[PDB]
Image (spheres, grey):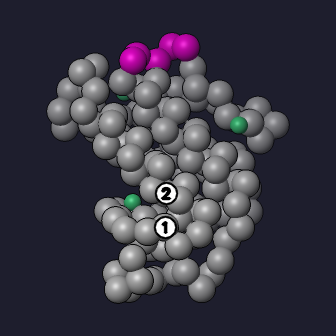
């Protein structure tokens, strides 16, 4: 679920404000997105979007009920490292890995404030 993704991002990037910093950035960071990612961070968001799309089509995820935004899973944060729990069901495990991959990606790429609030003309 989103507030677990927020937690993951704080795990890797304690100085971030994840629902602020990684929303409305580039062509992909935020609800929706299409076109050409403008930088590596935006590409992390592209990847995450694609992962959430796959999660929504997984046989093991019930339509709507198991959606990635509201489907809570189990994870932990240890020394700024994320673990997805083996206690998760298959749908939850998939979603947890989407979020883990993105939080790690966000932590490994530069943040370019000039890419905030891009108009879709740029995509
Ligand atoms: Ca997006
Ligand atoms: Ca759940
Ligand atoms: Cl990690």
Spatial separation of the CA atoms under disc 1 and disc 2: 8 Å
Ligand 3 found in image quarter: top right
Corner quadrant of residue 33:
bottom left
CB at mark 1 closer than 8 A to ligand 1? no
Q: At 31% from the left edge and 43% from the top edge, which residue is drawn?
A: 53
User: Picture coordinates of residue 22 (x, y %)?
Assistant: 53, 65
Corner quadrant of residue 62:
top left
The mark tally for this picture is 2
Q: At 34% from the left edge and 81% from the top edge, which residue is drawn?
A: 120
Dot 1 lies on which element? loop
**Main secondary structure type of the part rendered in magenta:** loop
Mark 2 sits on what residue? 45
Mark 1 sits on what residue? 37
Crowd class of label 2 (few under 14; some 14 to 19; many from 20; radius 10 Å): many
Q: Is residue 107 above or below residue 32?
A: above
Dot 2 lies on which element? helix
CB at mark 2 closer than 8 A to ligand 1? yes
Which quadrant holds the N terminus?
top left
108 magenta-colored? no
Q: At 27% from the left edge and 36% from the top edge, which residue is drawn?
A: 56
Left or right of 96 in this view: 41: right
In the rendering, which numbered label is found on residue 72?
A: none
């Amino acid at each position: 679920a989103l507030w677990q993704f927020n937690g993951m991002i704080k795990c890797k990037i304690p100085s971030s404000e994840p629902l602020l910093d990684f929303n409305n950035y580039g062509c992909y960071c935020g609800l929706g997105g299409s076109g050409t990612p403008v930088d590596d961070l935006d590409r992390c968001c592209q990847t995450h979007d694609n992962c959430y799309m796959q999660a929504m089509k997984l046989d093991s995820c019930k339509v709507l009920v198991d959606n990635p935004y509201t489907n809570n899973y189990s994870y932990s944060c240890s020394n700024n490292e994320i673990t997805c729990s083996s206690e998760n069901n298959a749908c939850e495990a998939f979603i947890c890995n989407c979020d883990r991959n993105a939080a790690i990606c966000f932590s490994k790429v530069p943040y370019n404030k000039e890419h905030k609030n891009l108009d879709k003309m740029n995509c």
